[PDB]
Amino acid sequence: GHKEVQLKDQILGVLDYLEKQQSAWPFLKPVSLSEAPDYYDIIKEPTDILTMRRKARHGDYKTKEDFGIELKRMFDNCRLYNAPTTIYFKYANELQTLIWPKYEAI
Ligand SMILES: Cc1nnc2c3ccccc3c(N[C@@H](C)[C@H](c3ccccc3)N(C)C)nn12
Ligand SMILES: [Cl-]
């Protein structure tokens, strides 16, 4: 109970730092089929910042690694789908590089 509360707050603190970065804005909501019709043929376990924040608020992450797996998957999904010239691919790398020390300190 108390260990989950401490972890929840730390995860939200990392998601707070993540969302105030300029490269975070495209990750604030899920991709739609209108803008990327074959996105969900390629990405089987989609995620985004708001989804992870809801999950964190509700107590869904029992451990730091449970959060880490999905955080990393947000970036990995993005680079799997998008070509290297896209802003999405480029921001996923900038944003992941920025957040990783914060995630590691959890
Ligand atoms: C993130 C991400 N990774 N791949 C994609 C993608 C691929 C092809 C076309 C569009 C996207 C994409 N669209 C973003 C701009 C778009 C958006 C709109 C408003 C606020 C936040 C985000 N989507 C996620 C709804 N966001 N996105
Ligand atoms: Cl809500």
Image (cartoon, rainbow, N blue to C red):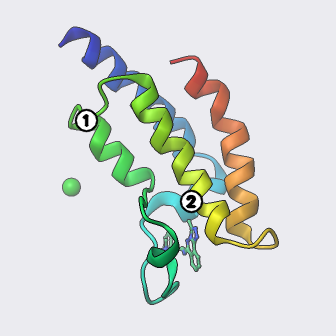
- Give the labeled residue for mark 1: 60
Q: Amino acid at mark 1?
A: Asp
Residue placed at 50% from the left, 34% from the top?
68
- Residue 7 percent location from the top left of the image: 35, 19
Indicate which disc residue 77 carries. 2
Residue placed at 25% from the left, 35% from the top?
60
Q: Is residue 65 left or right of residue 82?
A: left
The one nearer the camera, 68 or 12, is 68
Q: Quadrant of the N terminus?
A: top left
- Label 1 to label 2, Cα distance in Å? 21 Å
Q: Is residue 47 left or right of residue 89?
A: left
Report how many numbered discs are placed on residues in the image. Answer: 2
Helix, strand or loop at disc 1? Answer: loop
- Residue 2 percent location from the top left of the image: 22, 9
Q: Residues within 10 Å of mark 1 (few under 14, many from 20)?
A: some
Q: Residues within 10 Å of mark 2 (few under 14, many from 20)?
A: many
Residue placed at 55% from the left, 36% from the top?
17
